[PDB]
Length: 71
Ligand SMILES: [Zn+2]
Ligand SMILES: [Zn+2]
Image (tube, rainbow, N blue to C red):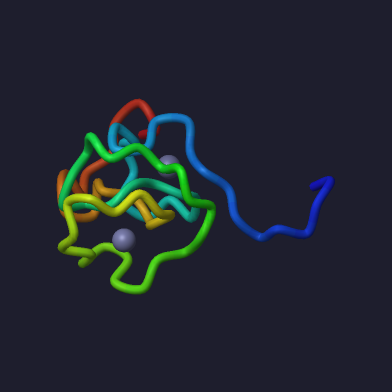
């Protein structure tokens, strides 16, 4: 990478199909808060705030723990 930031935000976000994905997705309590903040949040996959807009692991962990097309 060109900068040592250590943070990446994903192409699909709340629509990402694999539950173990290491990149950045929105709060699981709301799919319509896009990611604007380039920071790893504190509750991650249990962040209950519907107005958060930070970086989390994949929503497929609470949504659909079974991948397809990525499998
Ligand atoms: Zn992803
Ligand atoms: Zn959060």
